[PDB]
Amino acid sequence: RVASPSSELRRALEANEFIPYYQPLSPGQGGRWIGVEVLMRWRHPREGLIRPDLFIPFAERSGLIVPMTRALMRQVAEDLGGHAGKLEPGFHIGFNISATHCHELALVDDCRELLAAFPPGHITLVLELTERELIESSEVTDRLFDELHALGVKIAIDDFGTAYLRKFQVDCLKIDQSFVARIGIDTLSGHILDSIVELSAKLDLDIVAEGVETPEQRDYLAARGVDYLQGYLIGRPMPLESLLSSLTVQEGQG
Ligand SMILES: [Ca+2]
Ligand SMILES: [Ca+2]
Ligand SMILES: [Ca+2]
Image (tube, rainbow, N blue to C red; front, side, top):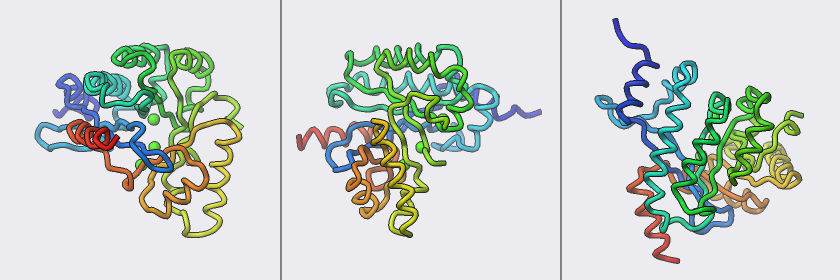
């Protein structure tokens, strides 16, 4: 017999094969990067550097998604806490969190630990949860979000648009790529996007647009006060080495 996907993931976790890639966040009006989104990559020993996408569902059912995320959080602290000079005060670091992680208070501890790797207030830690994940967690989010907020951690709604809004105290809305993709393709698409942006402003929330690929999209978004942009226009997820190099180039002109 052969070991299941979840068992293979466990072996990979114990051998430290899950590693962070870093996708840059840019201001809406341009300028130096203001943060990164952390992506999970698997340097598979015999199948090379990959995305564990097909494996994520298995990690969710087993629970292993939580310790996988923790291992990423620790590797980020190791990677970036020793280059905090290349990081402007306030630099955002965003993680994709799972619903399971919101049980008990482990997430508080995990964030404390990451924050301790940088000077107090030096980075802004952003935890990203989908609408679905927040609804799955509604019994715990009142207290959990209070403890995380107390530490200066922010909560973003991931893939937004993909009455419960009054059930959760969040900091940021991330506009799903599907909406950005349709900028210009038809007038309507836009109205709906305009409504999401305007809803952010009503609620005093920051806004990130995902999937920013063209200058037309960027300009449309920036004209409406979108705070932050992510997507191939700004940069693909990159290894640490490439991130530090780019950050060097940017201090270099500032
Ligand atoms: Ca998630
Ligand atoms: Ca997303
Ligand atoms: Ca993106």
